Image (tube, coloured by chain):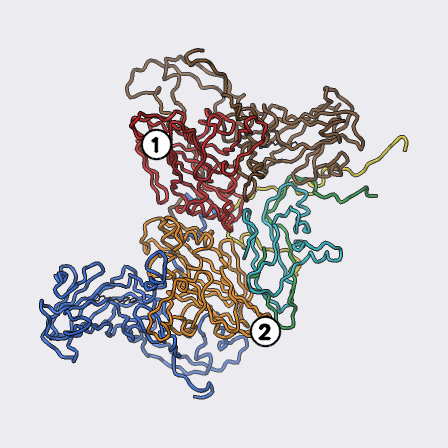
Chain colours: A green, B cyan, C brown, D yellow, E blue, F red, G orange
Amino acid sequence: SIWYQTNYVVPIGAPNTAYIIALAAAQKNFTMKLCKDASDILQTGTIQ
Amino acid sequence: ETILEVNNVPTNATSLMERLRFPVSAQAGKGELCAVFRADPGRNGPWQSTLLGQLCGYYTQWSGSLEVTFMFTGSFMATGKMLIAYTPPGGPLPKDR
Amino acid sequence: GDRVADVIESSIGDSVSRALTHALPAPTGQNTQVSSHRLDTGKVPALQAAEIGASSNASDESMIETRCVLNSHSTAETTLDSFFSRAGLVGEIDLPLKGTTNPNGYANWDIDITGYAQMRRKVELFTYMRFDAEFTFVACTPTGEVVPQLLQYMFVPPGAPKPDSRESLAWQTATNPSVFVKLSDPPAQVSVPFMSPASAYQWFYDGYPTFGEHKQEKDLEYGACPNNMMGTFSVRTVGTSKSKYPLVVRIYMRMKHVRAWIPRPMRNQNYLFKANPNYAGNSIKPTGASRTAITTL
Amino acid sequence: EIGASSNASDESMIETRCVLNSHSTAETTLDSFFSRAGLVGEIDLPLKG
Amino acid sequence: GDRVADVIESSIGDSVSRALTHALPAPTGQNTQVSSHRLDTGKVPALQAAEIGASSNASDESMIETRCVLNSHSTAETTLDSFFSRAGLVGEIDLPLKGTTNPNGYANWDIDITGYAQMRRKVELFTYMRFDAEFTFVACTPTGEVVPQLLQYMFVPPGAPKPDSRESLAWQTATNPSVFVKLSDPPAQVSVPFMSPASAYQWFYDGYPTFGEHKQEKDLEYGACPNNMMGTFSVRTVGTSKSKYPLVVRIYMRMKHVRAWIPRPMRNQNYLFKANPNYAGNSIKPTGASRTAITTL
Amino acid sequence: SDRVAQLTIGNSTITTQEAANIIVGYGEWPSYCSDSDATAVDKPTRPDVSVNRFYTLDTKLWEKSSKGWYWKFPDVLTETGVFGQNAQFHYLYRSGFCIHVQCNASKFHQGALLVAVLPEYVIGTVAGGTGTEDTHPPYKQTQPGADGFELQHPYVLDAGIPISQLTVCPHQWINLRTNNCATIIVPYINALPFDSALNHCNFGLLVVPISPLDYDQGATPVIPITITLAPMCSEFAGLRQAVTQ
Amino acid sequence: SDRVAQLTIGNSTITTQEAANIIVGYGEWPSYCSDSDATAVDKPTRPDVSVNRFYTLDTKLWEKSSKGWYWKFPDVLTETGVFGQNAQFHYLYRSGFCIHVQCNASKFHQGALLVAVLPEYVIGTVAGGTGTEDTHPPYKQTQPGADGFELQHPYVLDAGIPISQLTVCPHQWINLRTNNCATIIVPYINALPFDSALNHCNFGLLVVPISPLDYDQGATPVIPITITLAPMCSEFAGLRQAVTQ
Ligand SMILES: C[C@H](CCOc1ccc(I)cc1)CCN1CCN(c2ccncc2)C1=O
Ligand SMILES: C[C@H](CCOc1ccc(I)cc1)CCN1CCN(c2ccncc2)C1=O
């Protein structure tokens, strides 16, 4: 969860709204196991 | 790192690029809530936009710490302090800061 | 740094679990040693105090005059692998033509071996078990006849798409393991590893899988531990058209490389459901045969 | 903006204990991922068609 | 024993309080060294950042061209003992003949020195103080006359019976310390040790002396710390009959062997009560003199 | 010399002059989780004395017709003292236990209680009597809290298993003519290094009279049975707000 | 290099890119009580990470006319997280504190807050105005809890002493054109080794605007001030039932 600790303060002349971009990934202690097919299958009918 | 679609609400084609970023703006100083999302990487939701989330779908089990880096794209003159929290299992959606 | 005495001398953090007993080699039954009459005071092997919680330490030698007996009887057939490494039925999957169950030429079976008493009672002697396994699939028609039909078995791990039909895209099986075999071939057979996220599977879990209120409608989840749910086993006739023959698939499991912890009392009431130890209250029967009087055979 | 992923680790963001991680990375190698037979073609040879 | 790494390497228990500053000897004021013009970039002693919370480090030498000055001025008169070891009035006890106060020839005085501004303001510069003291008792009639009257002063520690009259049995003083002296003798004088149960007396205690609800009628106890209440000082004329003369006893205290901790701002509003820092709200005056304009003297 | 005993841990001390030794379950003492078995990365909190002490939670009355009772651990303590708080504020928990069941009578009373510890004590229902209804035990029966719960059918331990074989678990007997208490020390038992003190009960404590209590008219008829227990080597992790369930 | 900073303790981390160094009160770091200064004999409990972490308790709004506020320690935390529980269950308590007052604005705003720590901050009353009534401050004013309390007469710190000399106490200033936070570390201050966290407040935190907040119409007018604090080297003793006061 993300909360406002203080407040987005800006002076006269600058936008009252700005955006944040989130970038995620895994740490170096991350591993995976038990290979399986993905939940999605990107095909409806036959691919011609 | 890949872009996490925290703001996964818009669905019409013309507004899809808006999922890539969420906003912040001048508030009323009441420690208001900005956004929330589950940290589950292999679960439907924001994580599905990341390469981690997709690769994750090819494996039944995972283990490890995750990391999310937030980049503020406001103007240089804009300032602010945010509280980003991670609530381990059992803790319900925090009602307040 | 640590300066106050109570901190320096504390045992907070000791990861070495002190053990009071150690395993010794016992390939054969213990021998019997010679013994003679003993008319002593102070010595009293026959007298015990069961309250303590330990079994009697009294031996043959101390209760009667014994001879010497060199016991060479082996203890090998009572090891865990010897006991469990015997293939037994743990699943049956029906693929009928005209039916109420699977009249679509495919079937999904939740991997749970608790639907069969013989096997179930054996494993439930232990609380935790870690092991690998060898699965064998015996297929034929309901009369036990063998027909030229090709089948596909596929392992669908939790999170992978479960086929919804005989023609599902999921049968492309690009990542899931699949086995293609004919009913005419010998039984298919494969080795399966220990796949739980836990250090061991457990036949008993006294708790709930999630947090929150546990109201009536959610009591179906008491005792459900995801760590035991390994996924789905799917089977289909390999064709876009319905098979000409009704089929039956019997699934046999043979554990190997077994380890078990915490023994428990053995089931003495008939099983009713896979998911729990529920028993029929109106039919609580004694563990065994009964007689008319304690003073008569 | 630099283009690199965060270098921040668990140890530097919170007080951590020692954990000896023995989890294998073997099942995520290229061969482990791709060396699984999958359908890539279907050829029909019907009688009347 | 301790085995897990986080326990072995923890600092939980360090009783050695790391100090960032150490006291140096300073018997005299610092000397001034010679200095010359400096026309540098990067160097900037005059510029400070008060926000940090520290005082300026800029010195005379770095702000102007100075000569050499050997400063031999002493710092001795500003030590704690030099400042406090000066006897001052801390109590007055009246023993009138015909009166409304103590017309019985005896009086009980609660040992509290906060009834006198001069002394009080000095000690309140520090939060905690540990010291011994020398008490001097000056007695005479109200005109300052000396009369042949014998008196008895007695120290009644908390828990000892407070005399209830001039003839009380408590004046037997078998264990309490008492001083018998005539108004004609020089002032009585004795040494008192540091008697608190705490490592130091404290002129400010932000709390309550007991647990429980702290309702209106009990707010009289906010700030009351028993550790500062050393007992009662009792005085009487020595006789079963009333004295023929009215008396006044002035109590002077001179601290010695003083130690103080945590300096505080100094009182700037008139004192009103012994027990608290209450001030007159309708008369909040500036700390000092004022003027008409900031640009005029 | 094996009959007398004192158990001191934390700020609590227990005494007994009619004991029957001490049982250390499965032959091993409670120990903190090693750095190799552990998986969670955050530094744990090990309160020590404030939580590893003797708590006396409940007292039942033994009667000529009592059936027996059971308590679940750590369910019984989740709402008591500093241990409870730590169990609520933290997601992860692990610890051992020292259980001391008390019950004294006179040299003229008789009876025998079996005191045992059964790991993963899953409870079952009578399935509607005929065994056709797939009923399930309610939260108040699976996690009875400190009041424990009374066995409906002791012979099968309300779980379809013979109580006659319960002795295969760490246990002691309280035979009135012999002792007035049982003492069992239990290490952490689970297939995981830490778990939720709320959602998972590692084991259950069973106190069942196998030999019925008896005495003649005129002897004190009120024979209590008290349960005292102390956590051991308590470790907690995954901090956040308190949660009761 | 003195402007940037990260404070990590427990499972909490604070960052700032406009700091003004760190103040360590009276020149010394918090330390656990030594075996020679101690007097209580029971073994203490030192929770460590579960209690020594950053807690963000309150947010006030700085205005062109604000007078200033104060909070009492450890009063502010007695009802929060695991620290609160330990402070309630135990008679004795001692610890240090790391205080981080936050307040950011824009390069076009101006103002200066004085952030200080005053030990034994005893509060006084206006004595009925004329100074004849011997009034006393109510419990809600002496121990305001987490909401703190607003100064009635800042010039004299509601205690008859000049705020102009408050700088003689550990302090920092939050001058908007210079920094957006103050950081003060405070050791245990008392004439005793341990004390009640309930009946005695070791010190008070004062946040008073000396130079009034100002800005032109059009700039964000909502300038919050948030209080985050972390106990350090917390030690507790004299265990028993929980008590709120
Ligand atoms: C050995 C099986 C897993 C077999 O996995 C596969 C996987 C692929 C294939 I091809 C064949 C079998 C697990 C059996 N277990 C693990 C514990 N468990 C269980 C069932 C009901 N209640 C508790 C535990 C249970 O049924
Ligand atoms: C030096 C005195 C004790 C004098 O004790 C004796 C004892 C015997 C005799 I004969 C004379 C004097 C204590 C003074 N103090 C200690 C602190 N204190 C106090 C008063 C009001 N508010 C806080 C503290 C206060 O008034």
Q: Which residue bears the numbered disc 2?
A: G108
Regarding residue C81, the answer to whether it shows in the image is no
Residue D13 on image: x %, y %:
54, 55
User: Residue lying furthest bottom in this view?
Assistant: E296
Circle 1 SS class: strand
Q: Looking at numbered disc 1 in the image, what kind of residue is underneath it?
A: Ile
Q: Is residue E138 left or right of residue F186?
A: left
Regarding residue F142, the answer to whether it shows in the image is yes
Residue closer to the observer: G97 or E239: E239
Q: In this view, does B94 lie to the left or right of G120?
A: right
Looking at the rendering, the quadrant in which ligand 2 lies is bottom left
Which label was assigned to residue C89?
none
User: Residue lying furthest top in this view?
Assistant: C296
Residue B81 on image: x %, y %:
57, 63
Label 2: chain?
A: G
Residue E208 on image: x %, y %:
34, 60
Q: Looking at numbered disc 2 in the image, what kind of residue is underneath it?
A: Phe
Residue C55 on image: x %, y %:
41, 24
Q: Which residue bears the numbered disc 1?
A: F223
Q: Residues within 10 Å of mark 2 (few under 14, many from 20)?
A: some
Residue closer to the observer: E103 or B45: E103
Asked where in the image residue C227 lies, by quadrant, the reply is top right
User: Residue lying furthest right in this view?
Assistant: D48
Residue closer to the observer: E35 or E188: E188
